[PDB]
Image (cartoon, coloured by chain):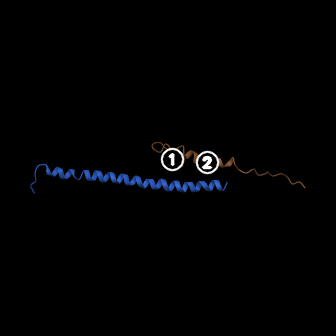
Amino acid sequence: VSGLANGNGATGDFAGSNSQMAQVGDGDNSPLMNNFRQYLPSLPQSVECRP
Amino acid sequence: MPVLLGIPLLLRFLGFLLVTLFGYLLTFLKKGFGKIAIAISLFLALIIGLNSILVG
């Protein structure tokens, strides 16, 4: 239960949730919340000012 | 106070099992107070961790 939170891993009966907890993620990168990023509205960029 | 030939050894044995079993309960108590040490540590480490991302 400590290894499914530290990110060290779990061996036993808690060995199925080691692939469910890889989808959650670690830090800022989350495989689950990066599925939403192929569908982001395309906003224009920033260029210098022309009259 | 006269007694039979085996009674004094039944009375010494019924207090060996008790001290052994009361010895195991102690071992397990101490283990469970170690879980609440791991738990607290974890929580405070996840807080200190988020801080370092956000301020960056």
Q: Colour of chain B?
A: blue
Q: Is residue A34 visible?
A: no
Residue at coordinates 33% horizontally, 53% vertically from top-left? B25
Q: Are marks 1 and 2 on the same chain?
A: yes
Q: Secondary structure at mark 1?
A: helix
Local secondary structure at mark 2: loop
Left/right of residue B22 with respect to residue B48 in the rendered view: left
Question: Which is more toward the observer, B9 or B42?
Answer: B42
Is mark 1 in CB contact (under 8 Å) with mark 2?
A: no
- The residue under the point 47% across, 55% down is B37
For marks 1 and 2, the one nearer the N-term is 1
User: Which chain does the numbered disc 2 sit on?
Assistant: A
Q: Which shade of the palette goes to chain A? A: brown
Q: Amino acid at mark 1?
A: Gly
Q: Residue at the far left: name it.
A: B2
- Mark 1 or mark 2, whichever is nearer to me: 2
Is residue B22 at all visible to an observer of this figure? Answer: yes
Residue bearing the label numbered 2: A32
Kindly identify which residue carries mark 1: A3
Give the amino acid type for the residue marked by disc 2 in the picture. Leu
Horizontal side, residue B50 vs residue B8: left or right = right
In the displayed structure image, the side of residue B53 where residue B14 appears, left or right = left
Across and down, in percent, residue B49 comes to 59, 54
Label 1: chain letter: A
Q: Name the spot of residue B26 as percent of width and height, x first.
A: 35, 54
Taking B53 as reference, is A18 left or right? left
How busy is the neighbourhood of tag 2: few (under 14 within 10 Å), some, or many (20 plus)?
Answer: few
Q: Which numbered marker is on residue B18? A: none
Residue depicted at 62% across the width and 56% down the height = B51
The x and y percentages for residue A26 are 59, 48
